[PDB]
Amino acid sequence: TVSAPATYGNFVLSPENAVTAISYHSILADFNSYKAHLTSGQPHLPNDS
Amino acid sequence: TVSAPATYGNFVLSPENAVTAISYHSILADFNSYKAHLTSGQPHLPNDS
Image (cartoon, rainbow over all chains, first blue to last red; front, side):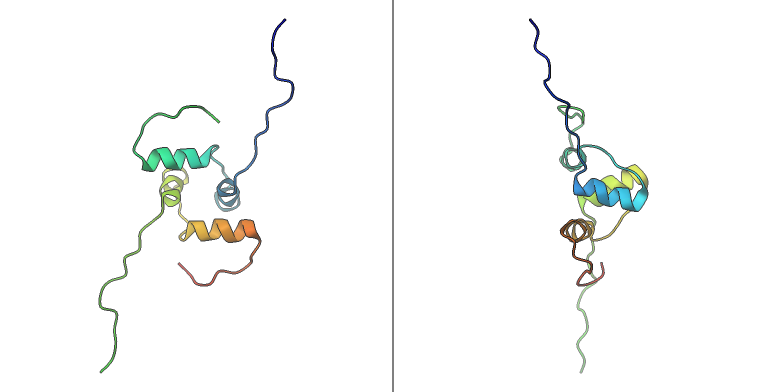
């Protein structure tokens, strides 16, 4: 007997993604994590989007 | 006698500007105001950047 995810995973646009979508036709996922770890001066992230 | 601004105006870019400049090579000034007013649905800004 094995454990499996009972439902699909949900991925959604944060508003900072939507504004970049409108402006430059592009989104970087997990945007706030990128900005926080960039301004904090740290190279590596805990998880991918 | 007339009043004048005593010092140059110090304008600095927010971290979202930094990450957008790194990624797409572009910046929207007063970026957080754009995000908040766009998401809230307010059509107009009080002042320019």
